[PDB]
């Protein structure tokens, strides 16, 4: 019974600003491609096998922060190091196009 | 396995970064300075922009000749002090052209200093140079260029806290007739650093409204990203010896937590009082940790 | 392979209230007095960690007017493996 | 019972890059900004199933469509090192 | 029962000035580098072994007073004696970058 | 039981300098000021684990990354002399 | 190796209330009447030291209207070693 | 082991310190004094 029971703390909610949370690390990840595939072919997979991805070659790649899609970029090579070039923040319409 | 002893003061910090925005600002400034020079000298100069050099300050200092006119300039609101270096050859050519000389005789420099008349001529040239540089920067980022001081030796400037600091040097070569000269523009990397993302990518034909709309939509897109928030109830200091003998049933004393720090991947975001709500460990948020 | 060499090194132990995963939206509109839950039922033993690595489990206990953690068990690697797996 | 879970669909992804950033950095990104990746060129791309890493493999393009060759399947020994 | 029980002494709190505490010795220490490493490699360590540090060579070193990071400097050699040259007091943002 | 504490992470540091100063002195430091170190050049740098000294060793750079060679591990006989 | 040579040299002995570690912030806002604690529970024997070196342990005792330290024990080096270690 | 008798009034206090700020003040003053 050490912990004190908190309740009724739903005072209000309003966005303050985006600098209170600024220096918080984000997990950025660029995605090469997607493919919907069942377990059928999944175990059929051996070493050296090739899995085709739904994404057409040369299309803009997807950029996610903490696993949430935010933007579409393009992959570039700078000094032998892989780099993405941000092209456009995705729209809600393409977000749902992605969902379906 | 490469393993060599650590020697201080060795040039081991290498930061190579292409600066396209500076690469175009240099040509814009060169065009502006060429017509300014045409307007002043009543001649036709050609200015070739050299490769931008990203080098430690003492390399730039040692490559400079002595004496050479150095023009400390303030690129406000950027904190720092840039340098405009006019070679003896260029000021000699300008003075020769202004004072009834068709540059027939070769330019001779033997460590001769600069008189008050030469200093005034250099000030007149530097006014055009600074106007051209400000106009060139105006396209990308509007800056005001102020001339604060002129010097002749290298040890009087010290615009870098340490001689091993990294600076960005752009040498231009100005040719008038057969005569030639050069002049450099050096900016400490501290001034450029807040504008690196602007100076790195090549400029795009957009507008300030479009740019602010871009990050606005991106900001709104970022908001829909789940985070991991971790609440720290207590932090007790134990020796390794206690940890090995530590076995179930022991009691490790802790102090009163007045407030509970909530951090995301280490960075604290909240301090809030602990509690229990709906059978769940709850926190009553007291204060968002603003910087 | 020395033993007395690191027999005395200090470590710092942390205990959590609980996990929770909540987006930038709710974090920005959190105000004073707002209440946020955690992923743990009130009663499970809290997780003790060192250098961000799981080390133990225990809950807070009130003896007189003083507080401490009553460790329940020590997690073997097998348990740690299922911790990461699920 | 294996027959039941031998037919179910699942979502497969392959990730090309991984970087850790603060928000000063994320906001600073504009249009055309290049973001460097911690991953070196040629290293095996992670392959994830519903966000769960199971394998590593190189990038290869077949018939003008993106693809990946399964170099190896990671044993949970490397999972400790993944964190 | 010799000691007298003191309580309720929370009158107020206000910074006075930094010269009341001035001639107090501080423990200044410059740090070469850091590295997160587990006990695994720790005992593997023998005499003559080399431990790589997270800090890149030639980067500014860290300066602490009583173990608290205050500034970043650069190492210099003056008259065969080691010396650090203070370059910049760290910012709260880099402080938290260090923390994470 | 050794297996439990044979895997735990710990924070390692190596300190290059050590100086004692008053605040007149600390405040007097400005930008670019050089602070001398009690430590002579070439003496073994202290190596600390969570702020606890265990060893002494020289500074060496490997593959453009800072490093240190463990010259010796200090026996607690020197700890009395460390204070 | 003389003995009567230093048999008479005087030493000064100090006794502490307790340790505490507190930053510049709280030290500067300490005002008159403010109360600060120490790392020791009221009742443990205080540490007696000479030239900043631990020598004994004892607490204050009231006999009549006079005060003195009642030494509890003498610390052997082994104890001193664990004092430094922990 | 170097051990020599203590002789007072001998120049034993050596304080060598580079003074860059004076090194530039000297040239500034020299230029002003020349004109």
Image (cartoon, coloured by chain):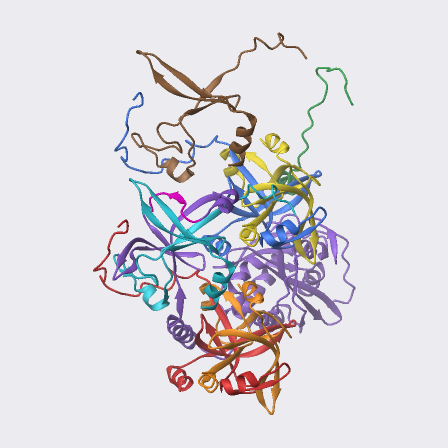
Chain colours: A red, B purple, C cyan, D orange, E blue, F yellow, G brown, H green
Establish if C32 lies above or below F13: below
Q: Name the residue furthest front.
A: D1
Q: Is residue B236 above or below residue B75?
A: above
Q: Residue at x 35, y 37 (%)?
A: G29
Residue B226 placement, left or right of E78: left
What is the x, y in percent for residue G71? 44, 19
Residue B215 in which image quadrant = bottom left
Q: Is residue B187 visible?
A: yes
Q: Is residue B236 above or below residue E16?
A: below
Q: Residue at x 47, y 46 (%)?
A: B246
For the C terminus of chain F, give its image quadrant. Answer: top right
**Which quadrant of the figure has residue B30?**
bottom right
Residue H18: % across, % down: 67, 37
Q: Residue at x 54, y 61 (%)?
A: B193
Left/right of residue G83 with respect to residue C1 in the rendered view: left
Tally the marks.
0
| Picture coordinates of residue B274, whole percent (x, y) | 30, 53
Where are the magenta residues, as a range?
B248-257
Residue B109 appears left or right of B273:
right
Q: Nearer the viewer, residue H27 or F28?
A: F28
- x then y, percent, for residue B122: 62, 59
Is residue B249 inside the magenta stretch? yes
Q: Is residue A36 visible?
A: no
Relative to residue B175, is residue C33 depicted above or below?
above
Q: Main secondary structure of the magenta part?
A: loop
Is G79 part of what is drawn in magenta?
no
């Amino acid at each position: 019974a050490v912990f004190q029971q908190l309740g009724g703390g739903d005072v209000s909610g309003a966005m303050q600003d985006i600098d209170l949370i600024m220096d918080i690390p984000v997990k950025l990840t660029v995605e090469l491609g997607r493919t919907r595939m069942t377990i059928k072919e999944l175990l059929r997979l051996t070493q050296g096998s090739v899995v085709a991805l739904d994404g057409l070659a040369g299309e803009p790649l997807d950029i996610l922060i903490n696993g949430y899609l935010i933007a579409q970029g393009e992959v570039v090579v700078v000094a032998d190091k892989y780099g993405v070039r941000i092209t456009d923040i995705i729209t809600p319409s393409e977000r749902m196009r992605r969902l379906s | 396995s490469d393993i060599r002893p650590y020697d201080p003061n060795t040039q081991r910090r290498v930061v190579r970064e292409r600066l396209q925005a500076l690469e175009i600002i240099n040509e814009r400034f060169a065009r502006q300075f060429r017509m300014g020079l045409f307007n002043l000298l009543r001649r036709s100069p050609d200015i070739t922009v050299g490769a931008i050099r990203i080098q430690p300050y003492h390399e730039f200092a040692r490559n400079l000749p002595v004496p050479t006119n150095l023009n400390l300039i303030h690129l406000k609101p950027l904190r720092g002090t840039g340098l405009v270096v006019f070679s003896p050859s260029l000021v000699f050519i300008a003075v020769d052209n202004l004072f009834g000389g068709d540059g027939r005789f070769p330019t001779k420099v033997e460590g001769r200093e600069f008189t008050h008349t030469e200093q005034r001529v250099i000030n007149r040239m530097l006014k055009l140079a600074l106007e051209g540089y400000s106009d060139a920067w105006k396209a990308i980022n509007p800056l005001e260029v102020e001339y604060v001081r002129s010097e002749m030796q290298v040890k009087f400037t010290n615009i870098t806290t340490s001689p091993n600091d990294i600076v960005v040097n752009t040498p231009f070569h100005v040719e008038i007739g057969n005569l030639t000269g050069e002049f450099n523009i050096c900016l400490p990397f501290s001034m450029i650093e807040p504008l690196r993302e602007l100076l790195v990518n090549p400029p795009l034909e957009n507008s300030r409204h479009e740019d602010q709309n871009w990050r606005d939509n991106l900001v709104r897109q970022v908001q829909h990203s789940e985070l991991e928030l971790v609440a720290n109830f207590a932090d007790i200091p134990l020796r390794l010896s206690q940890i090995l003998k530590l076995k179930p049933g022991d009691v490790l004393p802790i102090e009163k937590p007045d407030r509970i720090i909530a951090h995301v991947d280490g960075v604290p975001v909240l301090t809030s009082q602990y509690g229990t709500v709906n059978g769940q460990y709850a926190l009553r948020v007291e204060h968002l940790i603003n910087p």
